[PDB]
Length: 49
Length: 49
Length: 50
Image 1: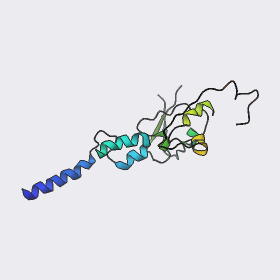
Image 2 (image 1 turned 90 degrees about the vertical axis):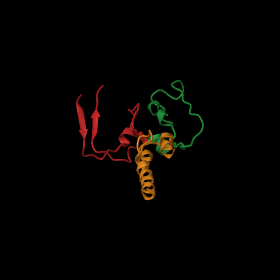
Image 3 (image 1 turned 120 degrees about the vertical axis):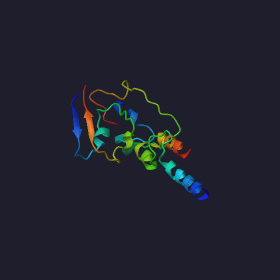
Image 4 (image 1 turned 180 degrees about the horizontal axis):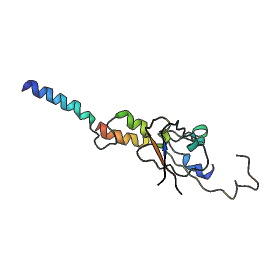
């Protein structure tokens, strides 16, 4: 259980990077490329939070 | 609903930005100012009056 | 500026005036003011000074 919990928490932390958190995309560079700096910052603030 | 299909093209938007008859650029999901940097699979046009 | 192009003045925009003539920074704090000038700038048979 000590091995499995420490593996499972790291797997969850890795898999959580595909989430959008209400933004348009989970890919960081796509928001920068598809939007200008007025709304790219407010879209990536959700990802950072 | 006569739709024009754009597949094999080099979409130069300098026509769209450097000519007089253009009024609104209402783009949803993408910024019009960065349209010359991206790529698209298939473009479709609905041109009516 | 010709009227149909007056929307080109914004932080982060492209076009003729927006690129080759007048670039605004993305962190611009200020105001942009425009009004029609048919009384003065528009002349008979074209005003070619601009």
